[PDB]
Length: 129
Ligand SMILES: Cc1cn([C@H]2C[C@H](OP(=O)(O)O)[C@@H](COP(=O)(O)O)O2)c(=O)[nH]c1=O
Ligand SMILES: [Ca+2]
Image (cartoon, rainbow, N blue to C red; front, side, top):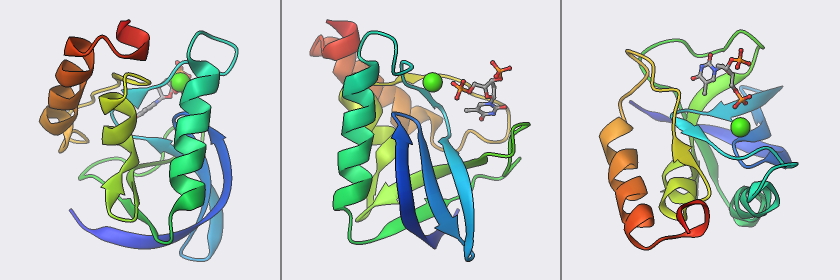
C-alpha cells in the first residue's frame, strides 16, 4: 500500500473525517474500525480523540487498501495517518474503537489493529473498562 497526500477540511466523529483528496472534498470512513456514535457511550471521547489527532497534524495522509475505495454512501475507505501515526490503529489502541467491518481484500492492516485491540482490552481502556 502507499500513502497519498490530503489536507483536513473538518473533523466529523471518531471514525469519519472530511478531507481534501486530489483537490476534492470527500468524507473518509476509517477502514477496519467502529467508534461509538456521538450519542452513545464513549462517542464524545472518540470524536474528541480523532479530532485532536487530525487537527494537530502537520501532515495528513490517506492510504487506500487493495479493494473498494468508496463505500455505498460515497465515503472514501482508507487508513488515515497523522504525522505518520495511523489514526485507525491509535483509536483502537486507546479503547475508543473496536476492530470491525473486516471485509475480504480491504483487510491489509487487520492483524496490526487486532494486536492494538488486545492491548487495549488488557489495560481495560475506555470501552473495555
Ligand atoms: C467501514 C466500512 C463501512 N461500510 C458500510 C457498512 C455499514 O452499512 P450500514 O449503514 O448499512 O450499517 C456502514 C457502517 O458505517 P458507520 O459505522 O459509519 O455507520 O458502512 C462499508 O461498506 N465498508 C467499510 O469498510
Ligand atoms: Ca461508527
